[PDB]
Image (cartoon, rainbow, N blue to C red; front, side, top):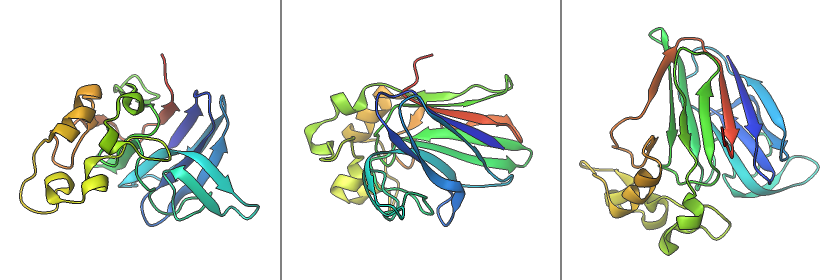
Length: 207
């Protein structure tokens, strides 16, 4: 399946694509404002994620650090990124269908639209100005808005035991982006698409 990753922001993003233990395609690439990158994701991939990284510093060998979404200091990600990261999440060819969502469970950095290229399903968007509205306690010093689990590290927020519920911090994200997951046990906002669809992930969407 193809995923067209389009940067419409007025800043560079270092796009990232991983399934947690390996890169998807090349795993990462610099996208200046206005640039696109099309990747191929293998059929059947479960637990894939695409995200933006901001304010990255890489050396000639592709090692360094990003202020949001860093994946082990690499340009070409093989693992998931450090919060805060708006996440495009997908599993493909699952019982004949593809499943897509956006999540704020690991915070928010860059606004995003995640849409199919087919008319057969509808996309998802989280593009409210979460960073400009971020409560002080959630603001991340290098940019972005952390989720409350990252900040507080208790099960109330991290959903590590029992049955967590919404909190005032999850509701901050959820009210701004009701089509994205706001905590681990949020009511799902996953979209069913025809199996083997193609997609576009747009940073700073407007259309």
